[PDB]
Amino acid sequence: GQAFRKFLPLFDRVLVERSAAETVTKGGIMLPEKSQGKVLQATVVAVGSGSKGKGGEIQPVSVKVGDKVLLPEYGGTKVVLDDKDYFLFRDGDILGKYVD
Amino acid sequence: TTPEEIAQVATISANGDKEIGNIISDAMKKVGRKGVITVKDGKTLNDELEIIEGMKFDRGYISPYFINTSKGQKCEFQDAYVLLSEKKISSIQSIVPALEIANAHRKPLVIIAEDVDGEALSTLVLNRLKVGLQVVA
């Protein structure tokens, strides 16, 4: 796997940083801080070593560092790193990734 | 057929008081002969006539942060957009496009609703105070 700011997740756990939630719309109308919601869009910043589905073989993590992914509404766990937020997820919990 | 006869009738029926007849004839001339006139208690010595034109209703603003004129502690706009709703406006998406169409045309917005709850109130007052767009509820 790959470690991000001295943190290597184990197994198939993936560490993501949630993107900045919107605070203004296209026409200039700006939003309150409470009603921004929880953003489901993030970028994969760290990948685990991969879960051992069967003995004698290792299954790598499908996503890689630098891929824009769509997080589910539920299932993440809190990670604090130098007073910054990050979220740990399972590999199968990520709904999909953005290619460009 | 003449307002003088109306003044005479209102003077005679009010125990010979000429001022009551004059003010009733003035009200008849102002709001029409078949008009809505209501008698109210006064806090001064002499009776007075107040003519209320347009639409007036006994409802105020939702939040006291919508005040822009400090002379009478009222809120005044000229050539303003008005939005109306029979139901209570609650969600963010139900109030944003009205703000977009008020900001794009650069016109004031007054929203007549039942009640505006916390999230839409926060959106309205934050857009009023931060960027300076004009809106009342």
Image: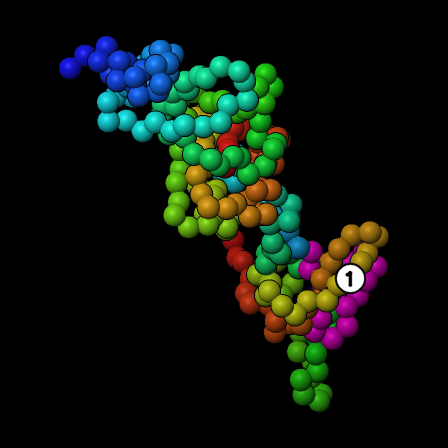
Q: Residue furthest bottom?
A: A55
The residue positioned 37% from the left and 14% from the top of the image is B17
- Residue highlighted by disc 1: A79
Residue B120, compared with residue B101, is above or below; it is below
Q: Quadrant of the N terminus of chain A?
A: bottom right
Q: Is residue B77 left or right of residue B26?
A: right
Looking at the image, what colour scheme do you see? rainbow
Q: Is residue B56 visible?
A: yes
Q: x, y (%) of residue B137? A: 50, 37
Which chain letter matches label 1? A
Nearer to the camera, B82 or A3: B82
Which residue type does callout 1 highlight? Val
Q: Position of residue B134 (x, y in %)?
A: 51, 28
Q: Quadrant of residue B120 in the image?
A: top right
Q: Residue at x 51, y 35 (%)?
A: B60
The answer to whether residue B130 is magenta is no
Q: Counting other residues with Cα less than 10 Å from the Cα at mark 1, is it few (<14), some (14-19), or many (20 or more)? A: some
**Residue at 24%, 22% in the rendered image:** B33
Residue A93, above or below B58: below
Viewer-closest of B61 and B106: B61
- The furthest residue to the left: B1
Q: For this rendering, which residue is in front, A28 or B67?
A: B67
**Most foreground residue, B24 or B94:** B24
B36 is higher (above) or lower (below) than B123: above
Where in the figure is residue A67, as x and y percent of width and height?
A: 61, 58
Could you tell me if residue A3 is visible in this image?
Answer: no
Instruction: Relative to B82, say whether A57 is above or below.
Output: below
- Does the magenta run of residues contain A11? yes
- Residue B112: x percent and y percent? 43, 39
Dominant secondary structure of the magenta stretch?
Answer: loop
Q: Which residue shows up at 71% across the image and 71% down it?
A: A13
Magenta span covers which residues? A4-17
